[PDB]
Image: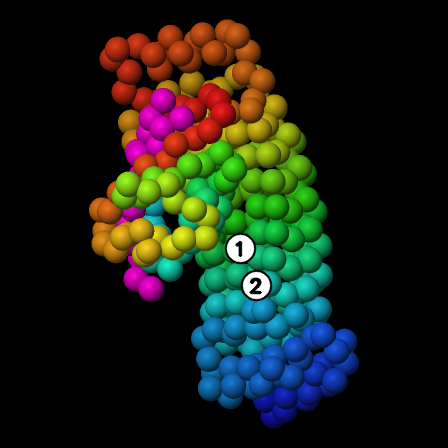
Amino acid sequence: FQDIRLWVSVEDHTVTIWLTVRPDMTVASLKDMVFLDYGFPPVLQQWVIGQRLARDQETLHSHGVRQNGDSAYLYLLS
Amino acid sequence: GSNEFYLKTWSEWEKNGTPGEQRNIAFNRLKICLQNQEAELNLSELDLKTLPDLPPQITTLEIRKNLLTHLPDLPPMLKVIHAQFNQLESLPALPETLEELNAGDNKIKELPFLPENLTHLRVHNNRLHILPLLPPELKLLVVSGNRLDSIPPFPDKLEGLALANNFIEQLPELPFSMNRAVLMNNNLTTLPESVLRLAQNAFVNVAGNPLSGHTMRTLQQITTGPDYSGPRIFFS
């Protein structure tokens, strides 16, 4: 329930963004946060966190996101 | 004697709701709030359709996810209002102490005057056609999903801007303080030159705008150049 700083590499052209997340956040809620803050529609977001393609209902905690500076890759679909 | 007025009003209000409204739980929280002189009133997620007179000492009003169409007068020390996910058609006059206002996901048609200490304004998913003049300490402006035809000039500490899914035809010049600008799905045909002067870590999303051919060449002559050090601009 402490904030985590997530390093995100976005590839559609690339950009690196810093997100602030909570470990109990679902991938669905992450997609919603990024939709509002960056404009990427949830249906077009594909999240990779540690060798796995993250599914909407999985938590960041379940994918090993635990400490500031942890990384995720975001790919944007056509 | 002041307390009796409030307890009486809340008492009367508790008995006049519809059966879905969790008025009894609200009455108890208001009571605890007033009698402990509590800083935050949290009536969120209590299916309320109106609110009564509010405890005058609160600095945070947490009323998200109810069914409110209007608010009562806002107590004059409020610093934070979380009113998102209601059915609000308008907001009352805003207290001068107000710093954060979240009224996203409502039905608001126009906003009242924005007070001079406001730093965060989140009013996405409303029905706004125009915005009030923006105050000088504003750091975050979230107005995506409205009906905005135009947007006022940006004050010079604005760091985050989201105005996606509007009808905006012209974008005012962007201050260097801006690190994040969501402009997607509007009616822009040109961009202000100041967009190229934002920081290298800055982000601009301008997808879904009918940017002209000359605009596209003008910008990409700079953004595709080898010595480019301006922000990352997403065009699609």
Query: Quarter holding the N terminus of chain B?
Result: bottom right
Q: In the image, is residue B76 above or below residue A42?
A: below
Q: Chain of mark 1?
A: B
Observer-nearest of B50 and A19: A19
Q: Is residue A5 left or right of residue B56?
A: left
The mark found on residue B185 in the picture is none
Q: Amino acid at mark 1?
A: Asn
> Can residue B53 be seen?
yes
Place residue A7 in its image quadrant: top left
Q: In the image, is residue B140 above or below residue B28?
A: above
Observer-nearest of B181 and A78: A78
Report the magenta stretch's main SS: strand
C-alpha span from label 1 to label 2 = 9 Å
Check disc 2: other Cα within 10 Å, few if <14, some if 14-19, many if 20+. many
Q: Position of residue B49 (x, y in %)?
A: 71, 69
Q: Amino acid at mark 2?
A: Arg
x 59%, y 27%: residue: B186
Residue range of the region highlighted in magenta in the rendering: A1-16
Q: Chain of mark 2?
A: B
Check disc 1: other Cα within 10 Å, few if <14, some if 14-19, many if 20+. some
Place residue B31 in its image quadrant: bottom right
Residue picked out by circle 1: B102
Q: Position of residue B187 (x, y in %)?
A: 61, 23
Residue picked out by circle 2: B64
Q: Nearer the viewer, mark 1 or mark 2?
A: 2
Q: Position of residue B147 (x, y in %)?
A: 66, 37
Is label 1 in contact with label 2 (beta carbons under 8 Å)?
yes
x 70%, y 47%: residue: B109
Same chain letter for marks 1 and 2: yes
Q: Position of residue A46 (x, y in %)?
A: 42, 37
